[PDB]
Structures are given as structure tokens and as C-alpha cells.
Image 1 (tube, chains in turn purple, brown):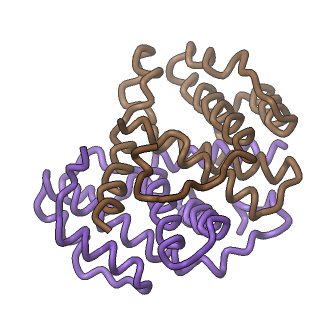
Image 2: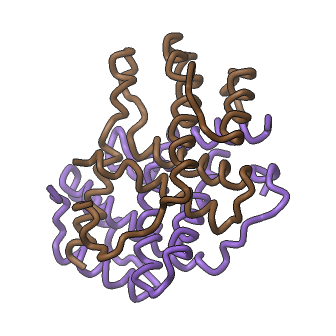
Length: 146
Length: 146
């Protein structure tokens, strides 16, 4: 259980790892990698459901999105598993959800620094579900949800 | 797709919501709710696997942990689903993973403010998997993973 404890401490370092792209825009306390992966996981869940997947598969897409950026704390990191979860069939949702998360955040930061919108423009998405959410996101450009 | 877009913007507000318990300890830029739910989801995944669950079920525990704190941005929030994902059978992992995440973070913040250790003490966990990770966490008290 020692290596599992080390891995959990290690996962916490993503709370301390800035999404660095925003820093040159002058955004001083940007989202962390953990924050990005949080919302990307929830978007991947939505993408899968909208693409006709079961809830069980949508949960796999979420989890795969959570695991996707763990390497940015540094296989290897995952040695404490002998095996090796199979995410190959939800990687499309993860890829699209990561890009859409970026675009959401670009829209949201554009209220402080107009240029942040660039991060949300010209995004290339693969799934129709992702392209539909993206269209609406860009047609509203309204991060006020309350 | 408009209400789904609003919900995704709304999910981003958890990146802006401090885990408030740490604030009175003098910790000025504490983990956000999103950061907490990120690592709690990964711990729930581990708990499920260690408790003899399939990877598919472990992914459901992760996702359930991700959804668990979404209400802190404010059912209702989830109206854009007609139905209603069934997480009842992984709620035990979510409950334990949320507490363990807290204890990890208490150990980690204890290097800046000794009192933060209190948050990791006297934690009541239900599963044997959670109790084993907790024991090792408290026996090492070493957040240096690198």
C-alpha cells in the first residue's frame, strides 16, 4: 500500500501544477492541471452520453480523462497496477473533451483578457457531439450561468 | 444543447470555489472544490479496485465522486438529463474517497500549518480498503513523492 499512498500524494501535485499556457497572457492564478482534468472528465461523460454510449461507458470516458494528464506531475507512475486499464475505446471522447474544456476556459478568461478567446478558436474536434457543444459555446460566448 | 453549455460553464465555477475549511487556518490559496473532487475521484477508483470491483465499476465510482460536489456551485442542476444515472452501489467508495482526499490534503498542508493535521485525524472510514490506505498515510506522514 506504500506505492499507492505515494501515487495519491503524487496526484495531489496536479493541484499545484498551473495550466501554463495562460501565464504568458498575464493570468496570474490560472486553473491547475487537476482543475482542467476535473471538468474535462465531466465533459467526456457528456460527450459519450450524447454519442449514444451507456452510462457505464460514459463513466469510463470520464475516468480516462482523469488519468490522461497524470503524467504532467513528472507507464511508470502506474507501476502499482500490474494491469493496465483498457481505455482505448473512449480515447476519442477524452481527446475531444480536453479540447472543449480548453475552449470553455478560453471563453471564460476572455472576460479578463480578450486574447484568451484565441485558445477557443480554430479548435479541431472529431465527434459530432463535440462539434455541437462547441457551436453553441461559441454562439453564446456567455460564461454567466447563474 | 444550450442548457448543457450552461452546465459546463457552471461546472467551471468549482475551479473558483475554495475548499473553505482551510481558510481559517490561514492557508490563503487553498485547493478548490474541483481539485478536491479530481483527486477524490481517482481515490474512489483505487478504493473500488482494491475492494474487488471491476475496472468498469471502479470508473463508475470515479464518476460518482466527480458528480458528488457539483451542487456546491450553488437535482435541478442536472435537469438536462431526463435520467438520472444510478450511482447507489458506488456511494460507499465516494464517501470514503472524499474523507481520504481530505486526510491526504491535511497531511500535505501540515508542512505549512501544523494544525492542518487535525483534518486527517479521527477520520471514520467504512471500507477495509480505505482503512488500509489511511493507516499507511498516517504511518508515513510523508507527502514527498518525488
